[PDB]
Length: 110
Length: 119
Image (cartoon, rainbow over the protein chains, first blue to last red):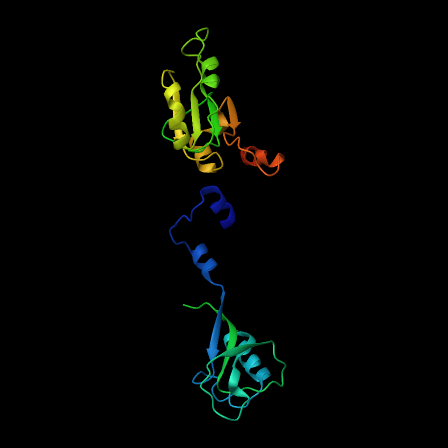
């Protein structure tokens, strides 16, 4: 419908807020979470990825689908590199480190 | 949009400031023949680039009912403003008579314009 409207006018037209549009507002968005100080802080210290996935889905209806992991995290020596790489859909028994980011789908709330 | 046009002629032109002239007077002269009464004359509205139409207006300013809507023939808003559903005829012309890498592709504009109006 928005495609047709843009095709008709070649512009984006404003409109007054109605309950139907406000209900249409509620969707899911792409986000990243840190395990340093969130509710999953204790679980991110050596816990498994599956427990995090289950807790996020059951509690906040959050869908975790990837780990953005610090590149120099498997090395014992400390490093100053802040680069991170992408791990898509890790298994249930995948281990977690506190310096990880979790891809997630947030639900809209007011 | 404020004025209401019914039983008129809409000439859509794919003009350009550097394209070759097509001599629009040869289209307006037969429609302004003296054997038609004044009330029988059909309003003519040119929809196209004003840069191209300024080069042609020198030979068109002596005719009674001619209007210009600066814009493009490929926009539904301009066609709705000119009441395309009540016109007697829509004439789609392509001024860009320049050579193209493929001969058939020279008709890429007009065909799409037609397929717009039918939809």
